[PDB]
Amino acid sequence: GLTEEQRMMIRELMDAQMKTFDTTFSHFKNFRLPGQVRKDLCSLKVSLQLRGEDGSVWNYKPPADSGGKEIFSLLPHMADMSTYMFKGIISFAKVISYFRDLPIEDQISLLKGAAFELCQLRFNTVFNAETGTWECGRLSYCLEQQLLLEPMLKFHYMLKKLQLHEEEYVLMQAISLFSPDRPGVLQHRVVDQLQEQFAITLKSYIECNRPQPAHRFLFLKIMAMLTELRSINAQHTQRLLRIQDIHPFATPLMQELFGI
Ligand SMILES: CC(C)[C@@H](NC(=O)CC(C)(C)O)C(=O)N1CC[C@](O)(c2ccc(Cl)cc2)C(C)(C)C1
């Protein structure tokens, strides 16, 4: 069985999840809309849909470029989504006692490392693998011959396949958040025992709640998924810095987290 402090751990995570993750995106408003290395971007093409309160529907089909400049038509908006996401992610971290109790300099450092990952983890819960779309309340972002060649895309598909519970998602969010090996983490021992206790909790939760043979090695699959995601996080920083080189798009908060 799952021990007392393990039940205690999950419950504080599930709580911070519900307090800070607006699953319907009700409060995403005031966002901008569309008025050489770029295989980076073209693999990530999406169409956008806004359902009005009243029943109206607005749709955006992006331009298939051969030229150069129209690939950016959607970055202002994406930069607005990301800011709104990162704010929820920060609120999530600060509502966790394990996190509050680290030194401030460590708070900042853990966040700057995992913000993207926690965010991609949340988007996975609103992803629909049948239709290749992220359903964000009134927004939908729909992927423009099955190409899991883009690591980020293969990540969402593979992870959705595992059909995790909300508790498994929030714990994954914890392991990723409390990673001992992120630039400028002073308290590497604490953050390391903390991560291990989250991992152990995940391991037990699975042993206890998923007894069926399809859920063999799930804990290990999840753990590999998280390793994959760290790799994708680093590749994405490099892509993003390249976009900044040629055009500033990053909101203040994105500059704060990506280190500029
Ligand atoms: C997973 C990927 C297809 C995409 N997601 C979406 O388009 C849908 C949604 C916004 C819901 O995540 C996404 O967030 N990535 C990472 C973030 C991204 O690299 C990016 C985001 C904001 C800026 Cl300013 C630049 C780049 C991207 C180009 C929008 C692609």
Image (tube, grey):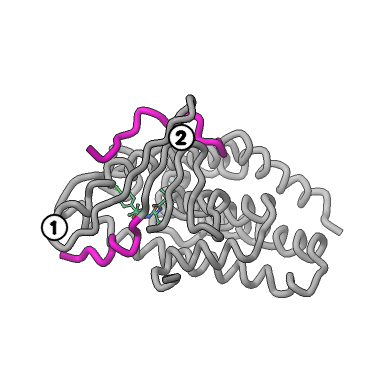
Task: Name which residue lies at 29% across and 49% down.
Answer: 259
Q: What label sits on residue 187 in the rendered view?
A: none
Provide residue 209's location: percent of width, then percent of height: 80, 60
Give the foreground label among 2 and 1.
2
Provide residue 41's location: percent of width, then percent of height: 28, 60
Q: Depth check: 147 or 247 in front?
A: 147
Q: Depth check: 232 or 26 in front?
A: 26
Q: What amino acid type should be assigned to the residue bearing mark 2?
A: Arg
Magenta segment, prevailing SS (helix, strand or loop): loop
Which image quarter: residue 185?
bottom left
Which image quarter: residue 64?
bottom left
Mark 2 / mark 1, whichever is N-terminal: 2
Q: Residue furthest top?
A: 54
> Which contiguous range is marked in magenta?
22-45
Q: What amino acid type should be assigned to the residue bearing mark 1?
A: Gly
Task: Name which residue lies at 48% across and 53% down.
Answer: 133
Q: Is residue 107 toward the left or the right of residue 205 in the image?
A: left
Task: Name which residue lies at 50% across and 50% down.
Answer: 123
Residue on which the image places disc 2: 51
